Amino acid sequence: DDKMQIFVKTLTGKTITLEVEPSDTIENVKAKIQDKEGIPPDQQRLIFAGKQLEDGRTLSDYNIQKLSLLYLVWRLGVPW
Amino acid sequence: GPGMDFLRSLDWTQVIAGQYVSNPRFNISDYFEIVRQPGDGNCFYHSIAELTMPNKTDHSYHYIKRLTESAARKYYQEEPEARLVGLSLEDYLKRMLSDNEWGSTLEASMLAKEMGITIIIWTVAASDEVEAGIKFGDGDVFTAVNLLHSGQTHFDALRILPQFE
Ligand code: NA
Image (cartoon, rainbow over all chains, first blue to last red):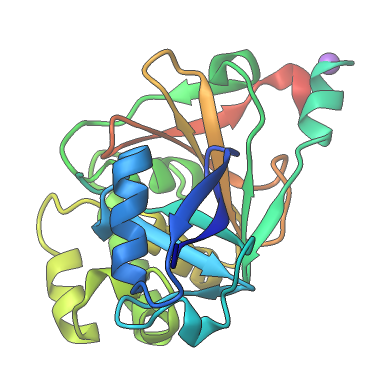
């Protein structure tokens, strides 16, 4: 439908697939990573082309189209 | 060696400016001595003090926290991970400097710059098996300040074992 596929390489070295919409907010994409991988949104650092993405933007604000590769790291040191 | 070969073959990916990730697979204690640190909430700074300060005691971490202050005043506003804190510079410092408040990869990034060192955090499962390393700075494992991270909030210090120096 209106959904595309993107890839996220996680801090653990796992290249996962994610189903998203270009209009999803970074916040929505974090929530999907929570569901698939259990990382709390508050902890996630989503990266695309060397930039850490911000919660009020959309994938499309970053020219993030189908089959894009993002990086997900997260904080270490704080509770979950 | 094969140990040295292994440590020399770590594959680091720069995910954002000056921050690198790798996913070697290994028992942390096969290559490092663990220097255990208290579980008082200050362990991040204890671990750093153990590796950077002579005659380290249970109160040396306060010095690391003060270096974190001066680091923050230069670097907090532009640190990507600071965005996740969501506090002004001054409110961050007040929280960061309070007693027994967890340190993290955010302070590691800033201390790397402030102390002119490379910091690696190896994050392990409860089996002490490595799930990833995150490196702040451009140095290698043999000269870096190596920290062991476990159980969400706990850090210990690491020293490479003599046979691999
Ligand atoms: Na060896």
